[PDB]
Length: 406
DNA sequence: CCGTAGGCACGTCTGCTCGGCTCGAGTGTTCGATCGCGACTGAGGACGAACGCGCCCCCACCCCCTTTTATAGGCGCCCT
Image (cartoon, rainbow, N blue to C red; front, side, top):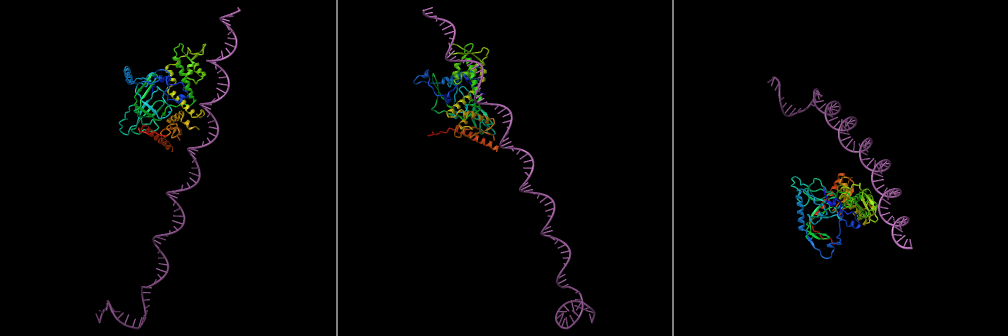
């Protein structure tokens, strides 16, 4: 059970962008430092980097007191955008080995760490302890390969994906800088996980699929309801211009569709007119709005449009998505293939063009039929096992390489 | 007679309707594969017929009964 932060659950901006142009899609999950137009750090010259130690201790203390003040047990702390800052709480880094994994979290979403352990035969004294995560004793593997007896494997686990992770040490040279309009802050950060290839648990839709079109529609609908809720006017009213600015690729006519059932156009002598909430229309509750569209569904959709943009950039037209190698790497194909195989509907290529590492240390998620048929499945498991073990060994290794001069 | 107001026209924006295109779903037909049945072949075992071997009988061949006579050494037995 995953409980996301309130800003994420509410699909607030900027945590959940309403629109992304080509540039943003290319930079998806890699935001570049952009200059500020105003505020302290818009100014030239040196700027102080501030310590956070007193602040970190204080927030931990305040949070624990709030915990004891009601009057123990479990509390949920991620209620406001302010609670999501890197400025307090314990922090880890996670570095993703896939250049563009099929699903990624937005800021404000939650994930668990699970410590998968397989018992040694006979008298097992229990799993080793880890600094992070909750131990899970598993007789069957949640991955493509099987755990060996006595093997502990850490992993990220959420509704988008499961992925093995490997704990490493941050280099002694490195610090985390947090940057706001107001100043820089610095934190020590020692724990950094390498993330291995994802096992997708959520299916990414194809471009212009019914699923995709239903999603943008519903997301637009949610944004609209939230606009009415934000309005302080009675009767509530919103401006077309504000919707168009958030959804610049929607025609005014398609926006009028979403508005015709809940609101009335009020014309004024000025090129700004209002849509006023109908007096017999009951605005959906917070709880009902949340049920309309989940953060996971937004993540699936984002994955599609970003991939679609990268494909266009590489010369692959919409008619391409009998199929080109590059199109096989698309998240709508890889997630579909992996999930089908998880349900026993087919097997996976494993060795193939969709291996995200390009060098045999990752899996190619491409459907092959279940179609000597005990040898067919034993060969699939053997190959899965080999790559599974290879990935764990390479990504957990502390060996120092050796810059490639090419 | 002069100035102000009103009306008309034009443009822009929004909404509604109509048409066209695309996508999806379902149903039907055709093709391929699998399964089943039958036939053939091969192998092994059993039964019957023919040939060979073994056993018994028969046949064949040779000498063994006797007589005669000349000759003469050695043996053993009868009663003188």
